[PDB]
Image (cartoon, coloured by chain):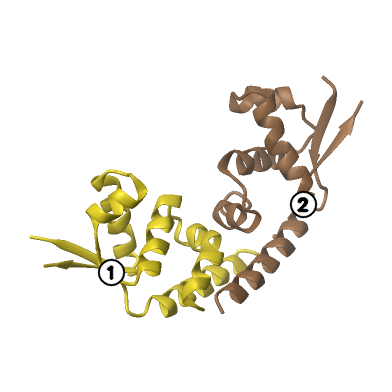
Chain colours: A brown, B yellow
Amino acid sequence: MKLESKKDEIRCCYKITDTDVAVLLKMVEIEKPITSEELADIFKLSKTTVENSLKKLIELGLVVRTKTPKYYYSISSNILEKIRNDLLNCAKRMELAAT
Amino acid sequence: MMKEKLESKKDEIRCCYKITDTDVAVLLKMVEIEKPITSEELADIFKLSKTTVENSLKKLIELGLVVRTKTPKYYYSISSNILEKIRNDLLNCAKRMELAAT
């Protein structure tokens, strides 16, 4: 595929919260691996809170974690294509629901 | 779409109109009862204040989903073409999403 201007679509298509989308987009822009404690300083939230978002994004295969702090998180190298496809499928499922 | 099927699409509806969970529950409850209702009756059902309820009603009215009728009463009811309106609104929502995938 901008990703910032598609916050609505993204939030709905994946059914995620505002914190989730905040965490995701931030990781996309820093273009580098990051810890849970760093993110927490960025959004001023508890590690646990932050980690809940990360978990949610990892299950969606948008974020990848890696052991060695303790864990590091990074965005999929092909993240933009994954979202493009995920939004196209969401639109198709939505058209079906509008039947 | 269908009458009792609206509840199953509550997430799409809420996200697409960008309304709250209260807004949607009010909408679905009105669809289910199939008769006009006062903001006072709705306040009792959800145990919310008259003002919170009317703020939801005002939004559903601006969305064209609900009709307000002055009768010293004020009754609210579902739009006659709610099923076609929601269908078309979701299709447009899905379209904006498809166009967002470009």
Residue drawn 45% across the image and 56% down it: B18
Instruction: Chain letter for mark 1, please.
Output: B
- Residues at marks 1 and 2 on the same chain: no
Q: Which mark is residue B77?
A: 1
Residue drawn 72% across the image and 57% down it: A83
Residue drawn 58% across the image and 56% down it: A12
Percent of width and height locating residue A54: 73, 37
The residue lying toward the viewer, choosing from B89 and A23, is B89
Q: Image height check: is B83 above or below A76?
A: below
Q: Image height check: is B46 above or below A40?
A: below
Instruction: Chain letter for mark 2, please.
Output: A
The residue lying toward the viewer, choosing from B6 and A86, is B6
Q: CA distance from mark 1 to mark 2?
A: 45 Å
Label 2 SS: helix
Q: Which mark is residue A79?
A: 2
Identify residue type, mark 2.
Answer: Ile
Q: Which mark is residue B38?
A: none
Q: Image height check: is A49 above or below A76?
A: above
Q: Quadrant of residue B17?
A: bottom left
Q: Nearer the viewer, mark 1 or mark 2?
A: 1
Label 1 SS: strand
Residue drawn 24% across the image and 47% down it: B50
Crowding at mark 2 (Cα within 10 Å: few <14, some 14-19, many 20+): some
Identify residue type, mark 1.
Answer: Ser
Tell me the quadrant of the picture where the C terminus of chain B can be found.
bottom right
Percent of width and height locating residue A73: 80, 34
Percent of width and height locating residue B54: 26, 52
